[PDB]
Figure 1: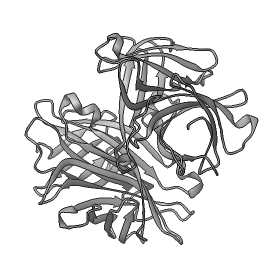
Figure 2: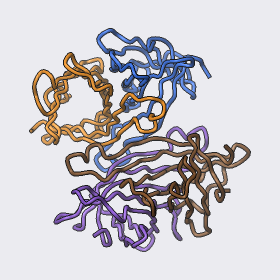
Figure 3: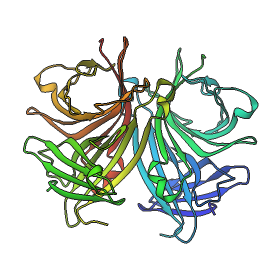
Length: 119
Length: 119
Length: 120
Length: 120
């Protein structure tokens, strides 16, 4: 149920393969949809989830460097897959920027994102 | 730099290798430190950080399932490596459990961990 | 604008008054809705926001103790009010429970709530 | 309780609070510069009947970053626990939300952690 293409509310797209061993690998593409807008992702999921209607736990990381650009920052998503007709990945994320020690206090943004199988 | 053996405040161990293409791979071992406590990690880091004194942004995920136990949860760590003598990795983390839709609102914990090369 | 009765997605009600000095005072009602589910809230908001089409920053706290129960915990919401056609207050929140030292690493939940003046 | 008094964080900030019998926290927060222009009102709540098993006392507070001398259009909320004793401490996480346009709300909220002690 996880492997495939997911869309968030703001225009982003994440293509992921969920391997049998717990691995997530894919590419995350930012709103521009550009080759310059593609980044690698890697994560982990619960490959033996409860079958009692509970969600499947997962997280992934994107570092925001590719061959064309580098924002010197890393986003991690933590969340759960929810299957069925209303299939959704519900997440919270933390975005950390590389800063100097004095600015370290304001290094990390926190948000949330919901992903769906259609836009 | 990043490649190595790090320890958090509480006794967990993070064995990581940082690769040229921006990959983090390794093993996370919880405080007990036996075989049943070893978990696979994956992540990313900025492989070309700023040269001005800023940290190196990075993130990883551990799904809390191995061959012996499955907690049906995943933590992601978002942070930065600060080099020099007294190298440290300062993070924030999100731990999400798989839950029913009714309990989702309390599926995620947040905290902070600091890692150093000394135990 | 902020003053009034607001509702989240999960059934709760935030009854708030925005004071001229930047105070928020009021009552937070969890989903059950009877008198054992009413708690005091206090908070602060930016009483002179920017005129560039930005939101209005605010936050508040509720400690989960009233005369009927005590959960030994407290939630704070940090957020912004966005006015407009369908006025809303977008927030993230942190819930901390009282714990021992050995358990303080799992003391804090994180989540987000969207409040509207229209009840779901 | 325990909580009433002056608390210092590592970055040079100071907060002076009074804990009321009914769960009120009121006071002032002073950022590192230390003068009038660096002083802000704080309001919050705490568990006035904590457990007696040695757990912490849950609490939280909010500061909106506006005084009579300046306005940053943001507010911070701290959620945490007081832990009493000889080395008393308030351990917190915080969220700092800034007022922004809709296009930038995704990037409105910083999260971090602060520990407050009674010695500077």
